[PDB]
Length: 19
Length: 130
Image (cartoon, each protein chain N blue to C red):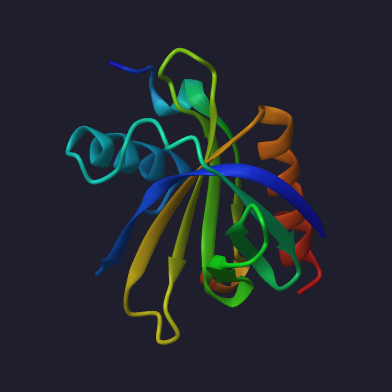
């Protein structure tokens, strides 16, 4: 179907409180 | 602190027990396949405000708040191309509740990639100041 997540991801932001 | 006009794809709420930005994208892709979320959002635009307090989503006349995603409860937000062929940019927000016992996924579609990235940058700066 659609391209893989790797080909589509731009950025992610993580809350260090739950990391 | 900044405001953006976005569209709302939908939410998957009250999940129990997705560690990795790639896993979240795949989870939502499959959720769309399984009818839990639309592939394309309704055209209705909402105002998304981003700040140190978190993310707020309101109707385009500001009369009504739809969602309040507080910084305390945001676990992660992933920005990605929907992969549907029109280059539309999505924001998938994973959040939890006061006791950190349940999780919900909220998915929005931005007007442009520049805006999606701008939203992520404000959020990342917000975490930085903590």
